[PDB]
Amino acid sequence: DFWPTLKDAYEPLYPQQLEILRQQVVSEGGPTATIQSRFNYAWGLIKSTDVNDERLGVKILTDIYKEAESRRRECLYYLTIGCYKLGEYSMAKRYVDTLFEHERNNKQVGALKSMVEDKIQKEENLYFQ
């Protein structure tokens, strides 16, 4: 499976498109909607520049991750990105490490893990200054 890049994650949708994604979920019954439609909305929210929307997207994605069964690996990658955008680096690290266990040779997962580790190391420096 080929996934979005971290660069892709910082390319927002038009507000009008994000609203169409929201309405699709509502039309499917919200929490009883398909995993795919809720995932699409969550990812749109994560891509938004608005931090409150990004937070909402990660919350939704965390909900559907628990329900996702076979799509759980994909969810972990997107969750890592969402947490990374929010500066939730400790959570991003946990998610990406779990994903890495089944994706040890995957270039995309390795790249994301390295970016997470960059930010973790940034904070680590502060405890010896």
Image (cartoon, rainbow, N blue to C red):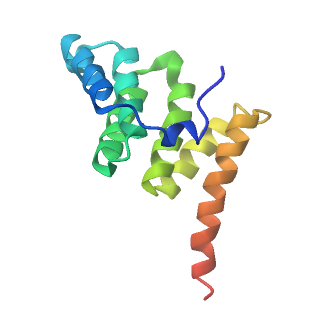
Q: Is residue 87 left or right of residue 119?
A: left
Residue toward you, 76 or 57: 57
Instruction: Please provide percent x and percent y for residue 9.
Output: 51, 39
Q: Quadrant of the N terminus?
A: top right
Residue 76 at what x, y percent from top left? 53, 34
Counting from the top left corner in percent of width and height, residue 5 is at 61, 36
Looking at the figure, which quarter contains the C terminus? bottom right
Q: Specify the farthest residue to the right.
A: 105
Residue 70: image x %, image y %? Answer: 52, 16
Question: Nearest the camera: 36 or 68?
Answer: 36
105 up-or-down from 20: above or below: below
Identity of the residue furthest to the bottom in this view: 129
The residue positioned 65% from the left and 44% from the top of the image is: 112
Q: Quadrant of residue 61?
A: top left
Instruction: Say how many tags the image has.
Output: 0
| Side (left or right) of 49 relative to 69 | left
The residue positioned 34% from the left and 22% from the top of the image is: 38
* Rendered view: 104 above or below 122: above
> 85 above or below 7?
below
Q: Quadrant of residue 32?
A: top left
The residue positioned 42% from the left and 37% from the top of the image is 12
What residue do we see at 37% from left, 41% from top? Answer: 48
64 vs 73, left or right, is left
